[PDB]
Image (cartoon, coloured by chain):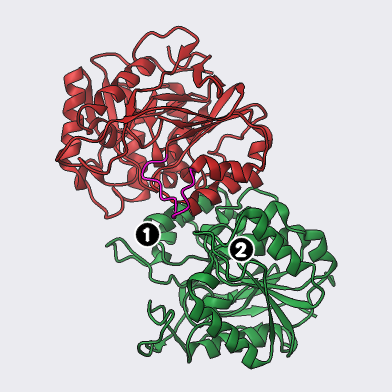
Chain colours: A green, B red
């Protein structure tokens, strides 16, 4: 059923940036100026949100200031794509104040990751328009060559180019999560050979829903969290956490019946994971929480904090094959 | 609403470690805690994971559940007390023997991460549980503060108390991050007050505990539903401004503040204000957006010393403007 979608990105389009949380545009000026320059050189225009350059310690501004910033982008018909500068923690503060009506009356590509999950999922829940787990300006497009160019490839392939369906999501050949080269480059990140992991064999087809699991706990139960439906594919990712923290998040899903409903799980890589001396991988901890319940599971998916990043539409039908390690998007996410 | 028997001198406290393996990593504080209580006249029965170690946790999901279940089903045990928190009590929730607890109610006590179990048993059984002392942090503390925490623990659980039961504020507190295993100096006596953040009175059933933890059980059958007129009791410890903003807004977008008649906010041990110089209550006031909810803050039922033993799931009367809290409903036999 033809069910409304944002317009594809085009060359020359204006991308609106906003800072719903951490004031990265103040604290990391070089990476920010670099990220801008990367996309401008590709041919896009950037429209700097009203909190760009601003500093309120752990945030860019008050809840009202940050809502006002995003709403001004949302109301702007000249903006085609709205992208967070970075995450943090405090995106969920904005949810009561977003102009959802405005967004529904002029759908745009909404993209970001990490803490922006609150907003991605909030907008999708209120408006039904799919949104995108993908690049945030500073971390993603501020990355030095070579990785930036793959992230950019995926960003273009999914939001600008036309794609016949089923659309296959190709595994990046290389990845990294090295904690270097933030503001200044000091050596080439290692180009590590990449793979996804077939943790539990099987196939599932269903609507993909998820994002950053830690952020989800900040919106769970509210009108801004979509209800997980029978047959959904759960997409989850965390970054720079430890084993205690993720066990809690996994058990949180378990005690909420999420794993009774989902047909399959896609787990992103865990940037800089701290296993607390256990040597356990995040999927092993999840598997203990799953207990005797068998669910097709594909891990170390490259849609998270690690580089490169894939752009994943949320709220659309996907097919995951955990045994052969494939993901295809089965329904249109843009027009 | 059935109720547990009051503690008595001579009873046995059963201890368990639903998360962090503190009896392994902190043997001196542990021993000291157990000796303090033995001296008072209680026995300690030591959970089957006592002394075990699995890095960030005491043991597997199944083993921790079995450890608590053995205590719940032991008729010789009057009080079940966590050794410490951590992060992972919520993992046990599917495996706990709620029906045995219900058929033989007893005192369930602890704080921090143990909120997952305090609320889950209450959600499942309707039996009141208690936000209060965990063995190692609470009773392994040195003088002077451990004796005030013990005074409160008797007042709620052992003493025969008339209704309404008045919960008094201590003279002095501390949150100094020293004297864990061994003493080195004395902690600073910080002079106390509770904070009339937003004036008013409210009477209603008290629900909450450690807010960070609550986000690990929210929306599940183990989280009691917040009803119209409930008093929200929330506490966080050793977090930062960003973290508690998220949790406050999490309550807001879930409609909690449309329903509760009052709030009671704990002190925030070693709070990190990220340079803002803002108090947690001020962050909460921003999130509240001028909604008029009576708000009493810096309540001493949290990670700071000393700690009050507060019942959960019972009628409470709070007066934020005159800084009083009374328990209005019987919580033990």
Identity of the residue drawn at 65% across and 30% down: B227
The residue drawn where x is 33% and y is 63% is: A275
Q: Is residue A6 above or below residue A244?
A: below
What distance separates the C-alpha of mark 2 from that of mark 1?
28 Å
Between residue A334 and residue B279, name the one nearer to us. Answer: B279
Q: Quadrant of residue A204?
A: bottom right
The chain identifier of the residue carrying mark 2 reads: A
The residue singled out by tag 1 in the image is: A243
Nearest the eye: A30 or A149:
A30
Q: Quadrant of the N terminus of chain A?
A: bottom right
Task: Kindly check if marks 2 and 1 are in contact, taking CB atoms under 8 A apart as contact.
Answer: no
Which sits earlier in the primary sequence, circle 2 or circle 1? 2
Q: State the image coordinates of residue B53 (x, y, percent, origin top left).
A: 23, 50
Q: Please give left or right for residue A200 compared with residue A152 in the image.
A: left
Q: Which residue is mark 2?
A: A20
> Which quadrant would the C terminus of chain A be assigned to in this image?
bottom right
**Relative vertical location of residue A73 with respect to residue A261 in this rendering, above or below:** below
């Amino acid at each position: 059923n033809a069910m409304p979608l944002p317009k594809s990105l085009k060359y020359g389009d204006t991308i609106g940036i906003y800072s719903p949380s951490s004031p990265v545009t103040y604290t990391s000026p070089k990476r920010f100026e670099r990220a801008k320059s990367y996309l401008l050189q590709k041919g896009f225009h950037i429209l700097e949100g009203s909190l760009t350059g601003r500093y309120d310690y752990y945030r860019s501004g008050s809840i009202q200031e940050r809502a006002k910033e995003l709403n001004a982008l949302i109301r702007n018909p000249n903006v085609s794509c709205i992208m967070s500068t970075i995450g943090g923690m405090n995106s969920n503060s904005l949810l009561p104040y977003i102009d959802y009506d405005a967004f529904q009356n002029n759908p745009k590509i909404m993209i970001g990751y990490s803490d922006a999950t609150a907003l991605l999922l909030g907008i999708y829940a209120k408006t039904g328009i799919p949104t995108f787990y993908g690049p945030a300006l500073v971390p993603s497009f501020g990355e030095f060559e070579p990785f930036v160019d793959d992230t950019y490839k995926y960003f273009l392939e999914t939001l600008l180019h036309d794609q016949a369906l089923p659309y296959n999501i190709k595994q990046p050949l290389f990845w990294s999560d090295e904690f270097i080269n933030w503001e200044e480059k000091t050596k080439e990140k290692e180009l590590r050979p990449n793979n996804w992991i077939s943790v539990t064999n099987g196939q599932a087809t269903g609507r993909v829903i998820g994002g950053n699991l830690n952020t989800i706990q900040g919106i769970w139960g509210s009108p801004y969290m979509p209800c997980i439906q029978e047959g959904d594919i759960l997409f989850i990712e965390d970054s720079s956490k430890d084993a205690a923290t993720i066990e809690r998040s996994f058990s949180f899903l378990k005690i909420n019946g999420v794993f009774d409903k989902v047909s399959g799980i896609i787990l992103g890589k865990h940037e800089q994971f701290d296993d607390c001396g256990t040597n356990r991988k995040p999927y092993e901890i999840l598997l203990e929480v799953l207990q005797n319940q068998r669910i097709p599971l594909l891990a170390d998916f490259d849609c998270c904090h690690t580089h490169p990043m894939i752009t994943m539409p949320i709220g659309v039908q996907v097919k995951m094959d955990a045994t052969n390690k494939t993901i295809h998007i089965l329904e249109k996410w843009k027009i």
